[PDB]
Image (cartoon, coloured by chain):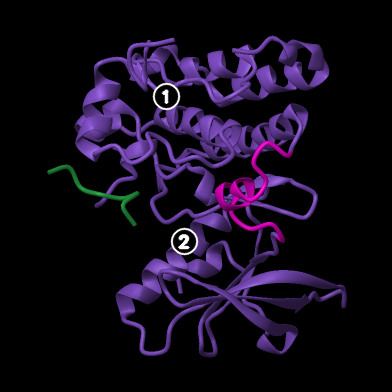
Amino acid sequence: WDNYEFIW
Amino acid sequence: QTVHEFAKELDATNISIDKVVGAGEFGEVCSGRLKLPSKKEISVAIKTLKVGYTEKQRRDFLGEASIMGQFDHPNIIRLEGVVTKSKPVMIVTEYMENGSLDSFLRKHDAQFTVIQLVGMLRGIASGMKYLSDMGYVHRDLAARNILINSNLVCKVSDFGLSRVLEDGKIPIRWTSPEAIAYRKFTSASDVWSYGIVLWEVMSYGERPYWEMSNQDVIKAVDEGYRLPPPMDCPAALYQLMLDCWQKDRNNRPKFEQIVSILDKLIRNPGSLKIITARPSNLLLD
């Protein structure tokens, strides 16, 4: 889900 | 293997699977029944490890059970036990009829009383008080990770990101600024997350920061912007959100203080009667 992401 | 320190091995003859009620990271989630040693029968959630699992998947699956089993509290999901000596490997937890809190509240927009919502929130805070007393930082505290039972009692779940306080992808919308900036995770970063949950609950499961770019959620919060008061939100509860969202983590309340605050509101319901034009969607301060 778009709820968890890295920082880009 | 390592999980038996904190998990009872169950006899699979005591487990009846009724229905596949979902799909988890590691295999399906089912509901069913567990016959206890006393011959009492209870409803349970049954998580199964997928056929053809990797050793890594097994360790991650059971590891979350190992953490959950360390907690015995009415507002933390209860681990009944595991099945490892037969396959599929299983994790059996207490049944929560109303599922995840965010999904539940979305079905009932504006249908509960403020005191009912405060009850939910107090239970969440009470579970977090215990988790933090035990030295764990959850790191994923969000309404989707709170489960709610037939009597509206709310319980902390999903210990996948949890770890002991000791010397990859993050839930950005729920994470404190310092934890985003440099991975400074503390019980005070869980208090930040709790403030977000408080907003989710009072918003009946609206998404925090709606569909803002992750980059803009990070920048905006860092600049001092905060989610705005939910419609008809008691002043006392919006203030609690703002306090949970203090830039300086040392100025946030402890979970014990949060529990105390909510208890006062429950005990003086008239408190909740005082209720909340700006240049932006997020509110500065």
Residue B280 position, x and y percent, is 33, 17
Pick the front one: B184 or B223? B223
Residue type at mark 2: give it: Glu
In the rendered image of the structure, the colour used to display chain B is purple
Pick the front one: B190 or B28? B28
Indicate the secondary structure of the residue bearing disc 1.
loop
Residue B98 position, x and y percent, is 69, 57
- Confirm whether residue B234 shows in the render: yes
Distance, label 2 to label 1, CA atoms, is 31 Å
Q: Which residue is mark 1?
A: B227
Query: Is the residue under label 1 in contact with that under label 2 (CB below 8 Å)?
Result: no
Say which chain is green. Answer: A
Q: Is residue B35 left or right of residue B231?
A: right
Q: Which residue is mark 2?
A: B64
- At x 52% / y 82%, what residue is drawn? B84
Residue B155 position, x and y percent, is 64, 47
Residue B4 falls in image quadrant = bottom right
Pick the front one: B127 or A2? A2
Residue type at mark 1: give it: Leu
The answer for which chain carries disc 2 is: B
* Crowd around label 2: few <14 · some 14–19 · many ≥20 (10 Å): some
- At x 34% / y 34%, what residue is drawn? B185
Range covered by the magenta-colored residues: B97-111
* Crowd around label 1: few <14 · some 14–19 · many ≥20 (10 Å): many
Pick the front one: B281 or B6? B281
Residue B58 position, x and y percent, is 39, 76
N-terminal-most mark, 2 or 1: 2
Q: Is residue B242 left or right of residue B214?
A: right
Tell me, for residue B152, which label it has, or none: none
